[PDB]
Amino acid sequence: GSGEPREEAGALGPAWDESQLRSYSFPTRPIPRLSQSDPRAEELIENEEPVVLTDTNLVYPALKWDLEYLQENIGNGDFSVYSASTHKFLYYDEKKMANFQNFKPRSNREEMKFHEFVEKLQDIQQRGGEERLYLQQTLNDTVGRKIVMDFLGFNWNWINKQQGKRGWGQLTSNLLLIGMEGNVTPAHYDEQQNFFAQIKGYKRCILFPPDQFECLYPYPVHHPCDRQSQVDFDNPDYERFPNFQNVVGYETVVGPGDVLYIPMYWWHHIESLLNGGITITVNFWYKGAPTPKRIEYPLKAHQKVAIMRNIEKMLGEALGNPQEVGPLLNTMIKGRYN
Amino acid sequence: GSGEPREEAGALGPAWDESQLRSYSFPTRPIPRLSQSDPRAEELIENEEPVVLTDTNLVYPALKWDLEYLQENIGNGDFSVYSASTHKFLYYDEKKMANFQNFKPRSNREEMKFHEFVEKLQDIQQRGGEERLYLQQTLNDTVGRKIVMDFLGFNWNWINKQQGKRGWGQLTSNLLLIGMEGNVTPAHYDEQQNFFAQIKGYKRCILFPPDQFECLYPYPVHHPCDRQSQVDFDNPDYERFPNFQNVVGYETVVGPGDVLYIPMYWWHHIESLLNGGITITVNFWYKGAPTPKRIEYPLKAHQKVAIMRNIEKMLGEALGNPQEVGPLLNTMIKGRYN
Ligand SMILES: O=C(O)Cc1cs/c(=N\C(=O)CS(=O)(=O)Cc2ccc3ccccc3c2)n1O
Ligand SMILES: O=C(O)Cc1cs/c(=N\C(=O)CS(=O)(=O)Cc2ccc3ccccc3c2)n1O
Ligand SMILES: [Zn+2]
Ligand SMILES: [Zn+2]
């Protein structure tokens, strides 16, 4: 798993204990925790494998952040706040909701000012209700001057060197994440390189390499939950998803000051620790390096995932209806390739 | 089936009787036999449905053909002669034999002069052996002057009008077919429009429309038997090919002077009648009409077959190995589209 819980400086006790981790059916092994000066960390990022960097100082000015400080300085912009009846915040593409009419969302999005989100959070704690909120908002110009000064204080020297040494594309987005304890972002994979900068609280990160595509059963590309696993990690249906019994993850717990490299196309299941308070995270997303001119074989697992995605996209446009993608694929292989 | 056997002119008896037809497990209904002046025959060809035209005079000068006449006038060119231990002449692409090493051919091709094929045929009848031969050769310049005169005597006025009225491409090939009684060309589909001009003997033609792709289970596109059905019509494996229990064919018996329009992508199973002597056929293959600019929906069945073919071709080149096409397709749909 995450190994033994780390001891905090000043003898302040264990940062967490195992009772704050949710229980699942699959084994894991630890993601390495290394210094940014460690060459092994450099070779992991280069080979697109996850690593937790403990001393980047990437978001050092943001480590003082909390709700009180942010509400006063984050400005009067709008923030996307997702609500959920349960602890699972399954994301859904609103653009693709037209393809699947028999899909009703379980986590409705709502725009609100930051002071409204802080107010709405404190009502749930007062009322003792079980409703959960998760702020997920991209940062921009509307933020106040002090947040701008903190942002400029980020270790741009280090992360821009990482961008150059890997040949990545440009920085596409900065996502601010503020979640309640026990909030779970279920397993999914992204298409860009991610630097996961933990700020407040602790998050358990369970990653799965791209070659376990067969064990995680993502939704159809045209489904609103595209790129997310169909498997309910809390109650896996081994009849529908038999190879989930073969899944093995990479696990770590990140805390304030840690940066987790989530490589492009790697599955990740992220949860804020139980009874751990609020969590704050800022992501750095970079387009991957361009596909090289001389195609080398055998193909990497994420390249085959890209191929499978393009086949499904091409079929949807070719047939004139994404719902015919399924039956044509079955017609193509039944009694011919299985 | 083929309906009642036709009575020949001059009270020469029935052209054939049902005992000369092989028995299969599927029902059929008759392909229409019409005059070329019948508008219904014109609308069948236009809508790409099979029809037997009884009075085209397409190969009228060739109706006098037999082994003796051809051997004397066909010239000293080489002829492709396929041999088979059984009555099934399953064709195999020699170019694709590299992809599947565990494939050994059952019908070896051999080049020989026409007088050698006639000699080799008469030895089998003398020795009483059960070996079977099937001459399948494209016609060209090397043929003698009298065969040239017969060829020029074909009803080019009619068939070139059909080429124009359908917007077909150019005439790509003329295949001369000389087979022994009981010879079976198992079920397969071609990609071009075919005018099937019967000359000597009788052939039972069983056709299946493109929308029965699911019932006929063709080989993988990269397999040497690409475009041929995997189902043994003589012993169908309902466990591997369950939807073959749903197959329904279009059936007719063509004789001297009949022309069968086999539409592009239609499956066809062709057999020379049992105890019917030798059969002679000449095919006319035309590239189909170009795909129209404004794509209309829903797609025709043969267009979806074209899509499935291109997906398999694209995967073979993308993965660098046609043998990885299967497992990737299974990975793509297992637990996601089935
Ligand atoms: O709670 C947690 O900490 C876990 C968690 C909460 S959100 C989340 N990821 C996303 O939101 C990203 S994505 O899924 O929309 C897909 C995507 C991928 C690259 C992009 C790059 C730029 C802009 C947008 C992008 C979007 N993770 O991993
Ligand atoms: O015994 C019988 O009468 C039944 C029978 C014996 S042969 C046969 N068909 C073929 O040979 C053709 S094909 O399979 O190679 C595929 C193809 C398709 C279009 C073409 C056009 C031009 C040149 C070559 C072509 C090749 N049929 O239907
Ligand atoms: Zn993500
Ligand atoms: Zn054919």
Image (spheres, coloured by chain):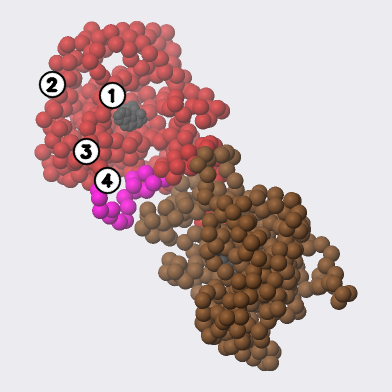
Chain colours: A brown, B red
Mark 2: give few (<14), some (14-19) or many (20+) Cα within 10 Å. Answer: some
Q: Position of residue B186 (x, y in %)?
A: 40, 31
Q: Are marks 2 and 4 on the same chain?
A: yes
Asked whether the beta carbons under mark 2 and mark 3 sit within 8 Å of each other, the answer is: no
Asked whether the beta carbons under mark 3 and mark 1 sit within 8 Å of each other, the answer is: no
CA–CA distance in space, label 1 to label 4: 26 Å
User: Relative to the observer, which residue lies in front, A301 or B118?
Assistant: A301
Ligand 2: quadrant of the figure: top left
Q: Are marks 1 and 4 on the same chain?
A: yes
**Left or right: A116 as drawn, with respect to A250:** left
Q: Which segment did they paint magenta?
A: B292-308
Q: Chain of mark 2?
A: B
Q: Which residue is disc 3 drawn over?
A: B168
Q: Earlier in the sequence, mark 3 or mark 1?
A: 3
Residue B175 is labelled as 1
The answer to whether the beta carbon of the residue marked 1 is less than 8 Å from any atom of ligand 2 is: yes
Residue B222 position (above or below residue A163): above
Q: Which residue is disc 2 drawn over?
A: B153
CA–CA distance in space, label 2 to label 3: 22 Å
Which residue is at a point 25% across and 53% down the rendered structure image? B294
Q: Earlier in the sequence, mark 2 or mark 1?
A: 2
Q: Position of residue B239 (x, y in %)?
A: 54, 43
As for residue A34 lying within the magenta part, the answer is no
Q: Nearer the viewer, mark 3 or mark 1?
A: 3
Q: Which residue is disc 4 drawn over?
A: B291
Residue A324 quadrant? bottom left
User: Relative to the observer, which residue lies in front, A72 or A316?
Assistant: A72
